[PDB]
Structure formats: C-alpha cells, structure tokens
Image (spheres, coloured by chain):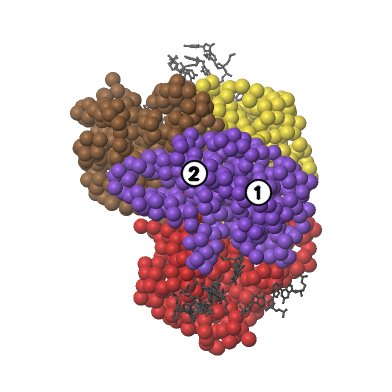
Chain colours: A purple, B brown, C yellow, D red
Amino acid sequence: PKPKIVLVGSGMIGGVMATLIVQKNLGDVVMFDVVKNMPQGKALDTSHSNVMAYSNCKVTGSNSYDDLKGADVVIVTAGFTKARDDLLPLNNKIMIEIGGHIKNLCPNAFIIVVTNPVDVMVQLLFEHSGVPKNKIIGLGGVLDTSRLKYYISQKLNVCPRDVNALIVGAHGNKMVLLKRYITVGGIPLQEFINNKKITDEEVEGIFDRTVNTALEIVNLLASPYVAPAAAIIEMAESYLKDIKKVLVCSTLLEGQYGHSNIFGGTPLVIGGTGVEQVIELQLNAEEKTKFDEAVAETKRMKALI
Amino acid sequence: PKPKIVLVGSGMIGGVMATLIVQKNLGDVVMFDVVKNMPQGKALDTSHSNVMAYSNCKVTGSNSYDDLKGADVVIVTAGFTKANRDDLLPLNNKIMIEIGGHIKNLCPNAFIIVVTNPVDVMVQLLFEHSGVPKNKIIGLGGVLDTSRLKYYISQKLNVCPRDVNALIVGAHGNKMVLLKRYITVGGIPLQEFINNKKITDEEVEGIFDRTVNTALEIVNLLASPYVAPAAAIIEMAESYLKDIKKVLVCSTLLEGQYGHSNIFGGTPLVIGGTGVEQVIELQLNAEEKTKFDEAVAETKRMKALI
Amino acid sequence: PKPKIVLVGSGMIGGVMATLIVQKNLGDVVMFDVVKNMPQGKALDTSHSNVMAYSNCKVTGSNSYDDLKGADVVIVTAGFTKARDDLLPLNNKIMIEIGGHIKNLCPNAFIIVVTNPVDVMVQLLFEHSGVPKNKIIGLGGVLDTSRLKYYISQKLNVCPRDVNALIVGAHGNKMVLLKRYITVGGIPLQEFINNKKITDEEVEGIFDRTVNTALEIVNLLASPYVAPAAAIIEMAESYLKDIKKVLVCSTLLEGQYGHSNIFGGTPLVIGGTGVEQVIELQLNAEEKTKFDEAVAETKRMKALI
Amino acid sequence: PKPKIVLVGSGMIGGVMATLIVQKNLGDVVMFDVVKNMPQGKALDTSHSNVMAYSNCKVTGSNSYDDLKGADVVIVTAGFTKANRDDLLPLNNKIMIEIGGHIKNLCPNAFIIVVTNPVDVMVQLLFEHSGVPKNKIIGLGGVLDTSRLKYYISQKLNVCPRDVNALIVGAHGNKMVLLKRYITVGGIPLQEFINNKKITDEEVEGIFDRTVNTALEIVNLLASPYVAPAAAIIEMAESYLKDIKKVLVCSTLLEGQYGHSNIFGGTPLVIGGTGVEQVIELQLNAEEKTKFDEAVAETKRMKALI
C-alpha cells in the first residue's frame, strides 16, 4: 500500500534520511546496519516524530539483510571510510553481498548507491544485483551542485534554488564543474560577471571550495550528512511521486561523452519507472577533456578491486 | 504579530488567493470587494478550511476600504474587465486613484502587488497615487506568463514543469517578449534539446503563440484564468513575507534599464523581506531589445489615454 | 505509476479540489462534467499552477464518462440542485449512470460521494456500482465538524485543529452534534465552561451556527465550495497515502447504532485499503435517539426516489 | 526581516533542529557551542540543504555568546550530562547564569525554550537570571513525552499517530503524570476502545511504563534521543514564530495552579505570537492531584541543591 524504503546503512546519513522520510510521509522505513543496537535505537527515536509531523510512516531497525524483502527503494550507505585505494576491495565485497540479497528479495527495487567512490560502487552493485540499467543510480551531482549553487547564491544574495549548475563526470576530486552552464534565475552567470556583481576569481574560488567542501567540514570537526541525505531524498522522492525532476546522478554510460561501460554523473530524469531519460550535454572540447579525466579516474580505481 | 494580507478584489482570483494563503498559513486575510455579500460569503467558507490545513489564519470579508489599515501586503485585482477595450482605462484609472488614496492613508508601508489589466499601466497609476516607494509595488506578469511557457515546454519534453526556466519580459499582454535564447531545461540550454530532435523550432514557436494567447484559449473554453494567476501572486507575496529572495519576473519601475524611464515594465527582480531588492537588467541583443521597445511603447500608448 | 483522480462534476467544489490536488502533488486529475467546454478551460488554467507548486500533475477536462477508465479515486459532486424532494429521482438516475460506468471502467476505485442528500446518494451509487462497502463513503462529518471546530477555536483563541468534535448520523439538518465529545487540545470542553472561558449559551449558539452554515453562506453568495473541497481532499489524501486518519464519514451501517441497510455518518479510519474500521460510538440514550432521527430522515428521503 | 534562531548547544538534538528549521524555512540559525569548530562544520553541511528544501536560511556556527545578539528565539540544550546526578545541578546552574547574563544584555526580547535536564529546574534558573517575562520562556517536556504515549496507542489501534491525544503533566522525568482519563483517539475517549476490547487496560499500563522509560530504552540501544526531542522543540518554536496558538504541554511558571507557586511545572498552554498566551489548569481529581504534587516536590528537591 505504502512504499517500503530500506536504508542499507544507518549512520549519520541514514539517520537524517529516516527523519526526512517521516517529515514528508514518504513511506515505511527499515533502518539496516551491521552494528547491532544502533538502528533499532534510531528507528524508535524517529518513529515518535510521526506525531509532530502528522505522518504515518513505520520506522523499524534491523540487522538482518532479509528485511530487504519487498523493498521499493534501497539506499546503500554501508561501507568502510578508513582502517585510501585500499578500501576498494573491501567495499567490493559489501556490494557483492548486498547485490546478492537485492537479487533475491527485492529484484524490482529502485537502488540509490552512496558508498564512495560512488561511480565505482554503483557499477559493482549494478552487476552483482542484476537490476536493470534504469533502476540503479549513484548520489553525486545533486550533492556537489547543491554546494556550488549555495555558495553562488550567497554571493549574489538570491534564493539558493534559483541558481542552477551542472557537475558531471564523477563525484569526487575529478568532478567537472561546467562554468558555461550556470544560471541565476534562468540568467547566464556571465551576465552577473559582466555586471561586476561577481568576479571570475570569486567563481574559481567557489569552484575550489565546492571540490573541497567535504574536507572543509571534516577539518571543522564534523562530517557531511545533512546535505547528502536531503540530496538522496530528493532523488527518491522524484521516483516515488513520479515527478520527473532533472537531476544529475551517476548512471550507466553506453556511448555518451565517448565512454561506454562505466558509470558517470550526467543529468537525468527520475520518474515513476526509474531513470526515464539520460541527457547527454553537448560539451565542447575543454569540457570533454575534463570529463574524460573524470571517467579515467573511475576506471583507474575500478581496475583495483 | 501575524502578517495582514488584504485582497482588494474578491473575484475568482481573490478566492483562490485566500484559499492558498490558508493552505500555506501565510497570514490573516481581508477579502475586500465593492459587491455587498460576496467577500463575506467567501471569507466564511474559506475560514473553515483552517481546520483541514492545520492553520490559524483569520479570514474576514469587507466592503469598507477602512479595512486596509495596518495591511502588510495589499493585492489589487479590482477593476473593470468589460463595459473598444482601451475604453476601460479611464474607468480603472479612477479606481486606482481611490485605492491609492486609502493605501496612502491607511497602510503607507504595505507591499503592493497590482493585478488589474493592463497591469504595466495600472501598477504605475497606483504607484503614483499611493506614493509608496519604488521597491514596495510591483505588477503581476512574468510569473504567470512564464508559468504557461514552462508548463507547455515541460510536457513536450516530459520533465517536471518547474525544471523549465524561461523569461518573458517587457509587458504582460500581447507584446510580451519571449526570450527563446534564455530557455533552459534542468539548467540546460533548450537549443540542445532542439539539436537532439527532442523538440523542433516549429513546436517552440507554436508554444510561444499558445502562451501569448493562453487567456483567450481558456475564455473560449467557457472558463477563465484564476488558479494560475493566484498561484503566481502567492509565490511573489510569499517571497516577500518569508524573505526568500526568489528571482521573479515582474512589472517594476524602469529608471534607465533597457533604455527606458518613468514607465513600468516586466524584468527579473529579487523579492525579499525589504521589497524589491534588485532590479536585474538582462543583456539583450539588438533584436530582443527591439521587441522590448515595442512592449514599452504599447504601455505608453495606453498610458496616454487615461 | 501516479494516481488518477477523476472529478465527476467540475463545479466550484471540483475547481478547488483540482487546485488542492496540484498543490499537494496527489495525482493526475480529470475534471469531468456534462457542461461541454468549461472543464477543459478549468483544467488548462489549473495545469499551469504545477509550476508554482513544484508538482507534476496532469490536469485535463472531459465530457465523456469513458475517462473514468483506470481511475484510482472518483469524487462525485455532479447533480441537480434546482429545476427539495423532487430532485431525488433525477439524481438517482445520475447515480445509476455513474454507477454503470464505474462498474465497467474503474470497478476497483475508491469512491467519495458529495451529491446531496449525501447519505441517500452514496447508498444509491453503492448499489448501482457494486463496489465493496469499504471503497465508497460520503462527505459529511469532516465538513460539518470543521465548522464546529473553527467556531469553538475562535471563542477560546486556540488553533482550530486543536479543537476536536464529532458530528454523526447524517449530513444535513438532522446532524447529531455530540456536545459530550468536544475536546480542546485533548481537554474536555466542559472544563472551559467551568472556567467561564465559554458559556453553554455560546456553545449552543455555535451549534445552531454549525447546523445553518450552508444556508448562511448560500444567502451571502452561493453553496460553499472551499471548505467542502479541503474536506474531500483530506479524506482522499488519507486513502492515497495510507495515513489511517479517523474521519467522520457516511458509511454503510450493518447494525451499528441499531440500524442496518442504510448509510450514516460515523467515525471511521481511512487507509490504503479504503475504510479500515467503522467505529461505533458508545452513545447514551438521548444521543441514540437523535441518531435515530437522522437515519429516519435518510430513509424517508430514500423512499421518494 | 527574517527571524534569527540561536541554538545554545549544537549537539545531536541541535543538529536535527537546524535540519528541521531549514526544511521548514523558519529562520536563520546560529549553532552555538563551547566545543570548538564543530558547530561551524555542522552549519556548513546544513546550509547546503537550503537547495533541496527550497528555502533561504543562513546557517552559521559560533563559539561566542556575542552571537545571541538580536536572537528572536533561543533554544537551550547545552549542559553537563556526566562527570549522583544531583552533583550536576550547581554546574548546570552556573551555565544558566552565564546564558541568562548574556540573554539579558543581547536579546532580552527573545522567546526562550529550555531543554537542559532536569528541565523544570533549569528553565526556572534561566528564568530568574535572564529576567525575561514569564510568558517568554518555557521548558520542553509534555510535547515530547506525549508523543511517545500517542505513538504507541496509535500503533495498537492502527490509527494515525496524531489522531491520538493525551496529556502528560507535572514534570519532565520519572515523576511525569500520565493522565489516562484524558486520552482520546480521534476525539473518542480511550475507554470506549477498552470496552470494545480493541485494547486492554493492561496493555495501556504497559504503554505507560514504556513511555516513562522511553529515554532509557533508547539510551541503552544508542544514546539520548534526539530526533523526537528536536521535532518537539521545533513544533513549539513554529507555534511561536507563526502565531498558530497551538495547545501544547510545556513547563511554565506556576502562580497558584494545582496549588503550587514559585515553581515550574508541565501543563497545557497556548503558544502564540506573543509567547505563552494561556496557561490551562486541568481540573484534576484527587488522585491525579496527588501525582502532580509529587512531580513538583521532586522539582523542588533538586532546585534546593543549586
């Protein structure tokens, strides 16, 4: 009746994901983790917030992969984040495990992968779970551009959502920031540079800040989880309510940008049947070079698993 | 304590405005009209929906301009729409004189959104008679017109309507300037979708003509536009009341931009807590600038007849 | 993929329903009516508001019952209101027409009837459409109590939703106002009478005002449309999102209150499967007497079809 | 223009508060704490979610009480919770003295919500050291406790959680008074469901114990709860900021009600635009009044140890 959202991974990102799912009355939630009491503690705390939010979403915790049965959405945040390339064979097992279960219990689910490096991890779980091309994507562009959009909006004093920006190729240090594609209220950013309301140095500074936003926060003695979770929930909500939002995520490339069996970030339309369109940007030569470097680094790491 | 929103005019647009204000819990509403029972009936009906909406907005009706007192937002839909069409301008001019007098006396610090058509003339008349500052009065135009264009495009490309961005400037009405160069989908230039054969240039020009004529398409179907107009006003009004600083295309006073002065015209603005916080001049090429000159010129033709 | 809501009747109530559906992104909308072009105009207007609402709901007009095909929710407001007892055989024939199509095109939909007298009509459409008891209900209690709730909240200066009240029996002049069941923020109304924050005379004034609110508004304007539409959408949203709200609605009585083979207003739970509970209030003898008068008047009108 | 909400304490509860404030576009957020850099990191993370939430709240971190300046809402979660628990009361008292000192100089006009436990003591201490009016400072308690009771009842009866109404008064903590007589489901007295055998009194008392112990149940599986407390505080704060006049059970100054004076205790109140607009004295029976008196007595015990 009501959709079943399984969070495979109940860390700080899953915590905020469960909170936002209840806030929006989006579906019943299973908080899975391999740690033994944490998800049931979080699920109990979170269940109570149904009262304050006027919702009726069940939130239960679990340590059994069997609770994936009948999942409509699976969100995978589980995986190692230290004790750097060294983690890839480890996270490669976790994807083999999860994919095995996905294949048996919820072969028909919509999968969002978050585990980093996401463009590698989403492909491994693609192959081991056997779900179709248009039912599995990785978080990346929505998060990266949310930072880029926000930093520009603060310089120009406009509402953050009114800045549009495109970040493609791959999530991470090789992300492709497409300066040509930035608009403010639908207006090309270059018009604001011409108007001296923002300088090219400031734009390149903001690009560097964007690329390093995860590390900026970690140095402040915290970690990014609120913005990633809201980004994940935006993609999941576009699926569950058939909104067909144009969102940049990591999807299977079958020729686009000149690359053919790797995952990369590109604008997509997320609708009720899943990925409904893959939109190939008409990049010029400089950008295709930076895109090719982004894909190349995805294949560097993929050859090491 | 809670903001006071006065709808000067309680027709179908004002009705949906009050309904949406209750849904969004935006503030107390006075539904004004010169007709004797219509606003009081609508307000009673609408007040009850606070229960379903989990809100606490008071909604009362009035036939007295004295209820403008202490208004924080004033929305003016009052005016004649028929009894060849320029003939209405002296009539609606006199209505703006009256409303402006009361605004000046009762809520001189209000934020004014004018809707009465032709809006680019009407918003200036009420600007002049009410004496409110330049940055506290605007006219509906771009949000409504572009909402149609965005929607018609979004359905052709099977994407979410809000993901289409478009600017329509100059004036609300037949001379609206449709800036094909500025249309994006998911932040992507529309021309890439034409290049990809996802939509043709002929289809885009059909959509432009459909947009320019959308009010008449609906009137011919034996209905009239009010839902989309009301939603557009509440978006503009919500950006002011909650200080969102949205970039919205509206009719504002031009003091040089595009080469025009002492006239109102549609251009992107930032609506924040202090009113209009920026007036954004698009860098139009020569042909777009020519069509903009025609829209303003048509606003000045009509303004000379009041 | 996305739910299909067919508004059978595109008058002033259907107008606000389509608006609120787009506002809440609840589903695609068909505005049906027998007046010919008017619904296509209203839907066109309404469709554009998707942009302001950040939703994606298709909104089309229709003059063909064939668009009931695959409807997930059908909301019936259509029917004669002039040109009294004499309208009942006419509106019966309309329910026969609608029921015939519901039976052939969307037999598995959730039906909400509004056409008055609702407790008669929802029974007639129940029998001609053949839908289960629990997939069809009539508007009444949610709308009537909203008036009672609002007026109490304004005297006590509290948030209208924080007043709770039950109005049962039938929609219309014989509605049963259960003074014993009124709470404010969960507190019995009697405690506010004792505190002299409201008097029994004022409560009884509010009772008459509630009973006469439809006719009060008709005299200033027309029949009410904003609040009925928000009430129908509250009931319809409870179905579509499996919220399991306790709402007072007109349902088939199979013994409760001592009545059978008739529809009457009583608290029920609306969830993903439709009516999930019918809650029989433990009324005292005097309330049970006033309930009998409401159903009795429902059957007198039903004998005149 | 836009409200300024200062979170004095940026732990796990404040984290969800900043998240929920951006989700609801309620105002700009200052995440204060004495632990250093950590709040600026959390604020940076949280700021970005403005994009997904369609809102415009500034979210910054701070380690300086000078950022209380111009606060419209102050929410106090800071305080010692470890390193018997009577031993923490003079410590957490001196923190209230510090916060109160700054409140008096920088934001004497704010609406204060105190959470530091034991809340009914701390909210009184902060009341006296800041000098804010009685109706501009309250403590978290009832909204949170009843959320558990409501949720569990609704899960046995299979109804929407919000449709259960219940009052829990006296004090936040182990002496909380669970008023079974006041429990309704969709406005129907709970007893009707017991009579109908849809839930037994025996199951109800299990739910009562579970509610009293929910904090400890979660602490053993995890830590102190943070999602529901933050949603509860934000419900109270939104009711203030949007003038909803919701009836919420919170800790307020008692000036005679229930037979008690110069003490704070949990009771239903109305939170509106001016703060506390009503204090509702439940007409408790003798045994309920006995349990209420015990809650205040335990608050007075701990207050005598500062």
Compared to C265, does D39 lie above or below?
below
Q: Which residue is mark 2?
A: A290
Choose the circle earlier in sequence order: 2 or 1: 2
Identify the residue shown where x is 49% and y is 48%.
A145
Identify the residue shown where x is 67% and y is 77%.
D287
Name the chain letter of the residue that bears numbered label 1.
A
Q: Are there few (<14), some (14-19), or many (20+) residues within 10 Å of tag 2? A: some
Foreground label between 2 and 1: 1
Spot occupied by residue C152 in the image (x, y as percentages of width and height)? 53, 55
Q: The residue tagged with tag 2: helix, strand or loop?
A: helix
Identify the mark at residue D39; answer none if there is no mark: none
Spot occupied by residue D60 in the image (x, y as percentages of width and height)? 44, 63
Q: Which residue is mark 1?
A: A303
Amino acid type shown at disc 2: Lys
Of residues D67 and C127, the one nearer the viewer is D67
Q: Are there few (<14), some (14-19), or many (20+) residues within 10 Å of tag 1? A: few
Amino acid type shown at disc 1: Ala
